[PDB]
Amino acid sequence: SNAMRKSDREAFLSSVLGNEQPPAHLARTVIEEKLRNAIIDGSLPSGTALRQQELATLFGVSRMPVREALRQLEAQSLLRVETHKGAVVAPLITEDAVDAYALRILLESEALRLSIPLLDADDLAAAASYIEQLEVETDFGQIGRLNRMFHLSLYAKTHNKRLMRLVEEGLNEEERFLRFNLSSMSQDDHWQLLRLAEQKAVEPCVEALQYHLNRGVQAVTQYLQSQ
Amino acid sequence: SNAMRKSDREAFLSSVLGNEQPPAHLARTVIEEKLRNAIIDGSLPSGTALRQQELATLFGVSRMPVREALRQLEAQSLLRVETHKGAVVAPLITEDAVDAYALRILLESEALRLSIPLLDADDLAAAASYIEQLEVETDFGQIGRLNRMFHLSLYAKTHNKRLMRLVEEGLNEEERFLRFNLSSMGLGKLSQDDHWQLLRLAEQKAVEPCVEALQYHLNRGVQAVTQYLQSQKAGNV
Amino acid sequence: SNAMRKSDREAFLSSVLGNEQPPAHLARTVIEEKLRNAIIDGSLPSGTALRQQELATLFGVSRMPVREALRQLEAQSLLRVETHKGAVVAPLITEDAVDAYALRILLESEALRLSIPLLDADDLAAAASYIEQLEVETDFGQIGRLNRMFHLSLYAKTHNKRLMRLVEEGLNEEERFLRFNLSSMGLGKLSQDDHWQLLRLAEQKAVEPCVEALQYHLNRGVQAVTQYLQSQKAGNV
Amino acid sequence: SNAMRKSDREAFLSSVLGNEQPPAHLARTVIEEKLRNAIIDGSLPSGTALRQQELATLFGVSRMPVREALRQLEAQSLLRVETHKGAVVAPLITEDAVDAYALRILLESEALRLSIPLLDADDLAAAASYIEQLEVETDFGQIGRLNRMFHLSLYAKTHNKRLMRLVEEGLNEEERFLRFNLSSMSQDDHWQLLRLAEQKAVEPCVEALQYHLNRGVQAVTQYLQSQ
Ligand code: NI
Ligand code: NI
Ligand code: NI
Ligand code: NI
């Protein structure tokens, strides 16, 4: 680490955790609790460095109770060790889904604005067919497949092969998620996307996709929190 | 496929490849060469379906020499098998470069948008240091490395791990490319002016001006790569 | 040499090696073994002159088997040729370790004296970071590397390039040693307490207290190495 | 580089060079002059980073005149490029000799305090013989050899072989220097060293050696400056 970064981190930890000195005999417990709470409510974000001497100084204690607080946080999967970083706050259970959906919004918005201008009658008919099959489908495994196919039909004229490979990969991952989880967790948005693609209303279609994916990530994260 | 698409592909293949029936003993060699020639000169574009029976029919041969031909093409990386499509014509290196840079513009612009508002004094100090090393660097190997570290410095606060893996993959690929090709590109003396502009705009947290500058920088990159690859194809290197 | 030194060496060699005259066909093997045994058990100390005629005389043989013997010893690194001295008994690994650590105490203490008053906030931040990485490190390879970087951090403002080359040579040698041997040393769980103390004293610019702590740290190092090497010699590893 | 280090360097460059903005047309010349003078008189020590943008900001100019000032400094050998550092102030011609003698003082002081306690009559006689031969020697190549031999005779009982190898190496380097340079550039100090070693006055002997080597480095650096 670097001096300015280190001092900025120390100021940040103080603003989030405070600087009250616990009794020596309460230090192990009090520090674990304050760290856990700050981690769980997001005020100490993932990737924040958890340095024994920085925390011992902040709280006016020896390193040992900090070290033993950090050990329990790791047992609880709230901290992990990374190479060149030491102990850092671990990602919350929703983080990867947030990242995944953010990336899909970036990639698919681009696939959609390349494809819409070029979609032909055959593309638009295949898309209509997939939504129509979605309307009457009851099998949860078939729902994930058809939703995938629908979204892929809108990207049928995306003319960047590297982009498309990443797009498919995200859609495959989503299908796998829905096949295994949708049981345990509405075509109007799909029709709207189709209507806007038919009209070649490119950015309105993209905006509609972003809204659709942002509802998706909210449903996924809510479900992961549920467990 | 359906009757219309099939039929259109068959007429198209005839227009590009003709329909002389080679003798049996020459069918594989004749067909491998016609398809390779047509792929390389762009007349059979990437994504074209290469179907054994369609091609056997066109050339008046059996599937066997067509299948052998297409295996040689796959071994040369001029065709790839894709699920639901079969054997299709693969993108050539120039098309792949064009798609690669378009994707880096897409990915790196978002990285910049996310990172710029959060960059700390150490990030900015690191970036300046790398440009300063670029200013006095003479080894070509080191130029690729220092260039990559500069761009990574500006993305240092991109807190999407999935996005950053793709951004880094792209930067590593560039570095590897420059590592081997830069001394053959003949670009002359290089200037740090663009890097300094990128850093200045990053420092001021001028986010869209910075994105615009990166888009210029990357579009000059793909133009340079593209020109080089055509030189290399022509044998003018 | 002169008559007295020669004569004393000759009596000494007899006291250590005896004087049985081996048969000709066994002279080389007998002599190589007696000298090697006596070198390894310390009874012929490092720096002892090994002179062909003196040894031929003692054993009642010709110079040839003595010369062959001494060549085998040189090939085993148990003797070295030095200018003005000839073939002398080489230091064994334990003596060499003892001399190496004494020299690091000498060199590193001066490095610390020169560097401590000048260390900047980035130097101190780097040092803390390395100890913090040592605290949570489980790979033995990485422990040697992180240990070396910590010590180098404290010497970061030693502005004598000749001294620093020797200091770095010593630290690289330690790292290389730990890289291969640490997992076999059985030292148990290791503590960062000494490193933190060194940094604390460096931060306060308590120069002689810091030197004293480093001297303790290095003397525990040579004791550990020495014990390990004897284990290794005994075959108790 | 790191943020705090960079800002400390910027403050340092300002205290040494000032911050007066030259006319655009004088920038190239004025900056070269101020840098050269600060380098030659030691106020910008060797290893100081010379960063085009830092200097352009300091002087309120564009990078080009700084870049062209730095290029002339390099032509004059006052700056050199180092890996991971960029352009740095180069060592002055006396720097390596200062380093060499500093290191000899460290190593030889230790050889001397290991050896003096153990020196015997034969050692002390060999040492006396070398000084006596130095007193009557007129050949400059023989003077360097005998001075070496004298100093080695005092280290005859140094019982660290690694140390001794470094010591010999420094003495060899000195002998080579004196063989080639002494022409173009006094046994009382030698006798004093011998007298103190005879008495086993260990630290006084070491102090006397340090004084001897510090006069040596002063003569060597003075001569290098002369050219
Ligand atoms: Ni959907
Ligand atoms: Ni660049
Ligand atoms: Ni250590
Ligand atoms: Ni002298």
Image (spheres, coloured by chain):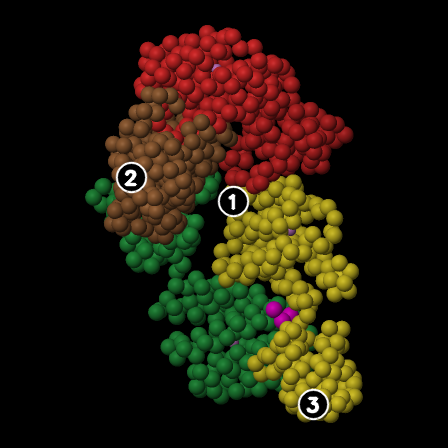
Chain colours: A green, B yellow, C brown, D red
The location of residue A90, given as percent across then percent down, is 39, 57
The CA distance from mark 2 to mark 1 is 81 Å
Label 2 element class? loop
The answer to whether dots 3 and 2 both sit on one chain is no
Q: Quadrant of the N terminus of chain C?
A: top left
Q: Is residue B23 above or below residue C163?
A: below
Of the two numbered discs 2 and 1 in the rendering, the one whose residue sits closer to the viewer = 2
Magenta residue span: A158-162
Residue B211 visible, this orientation: no
Q: Which mark is residue B3?
A: none
Compared across the picture, whether D41 is left or right of B16 comes to: left
Q: Name the subunit of mark 1.
A: B
The location of residue B78, given as percent across then percent down, is 66, 74
The location of residue A172, given as percent across then percent down, is 50, 75
For mark 2, does the 10 Å Cα neighbourhood hold few (<14), some (14 to 19), or many (20 or more) residues? some
Q: Residue at x 34, y 44 (%)?
A: C24
Q: Residue at x 70, y 87 (%)?
A: B55
Q: Is residue C36 above or below residue A168?
A: above
Residue A5 visible, this orientation: yes
The location of residue C218, given as percent across then percent down, is 33, 35
In the picture of the structure, the residue carrying the numbered disc 1 is B120
Q: Name the subunit of mark 3.
A: B
Q: Amino acid at mark 1?
A: Asp
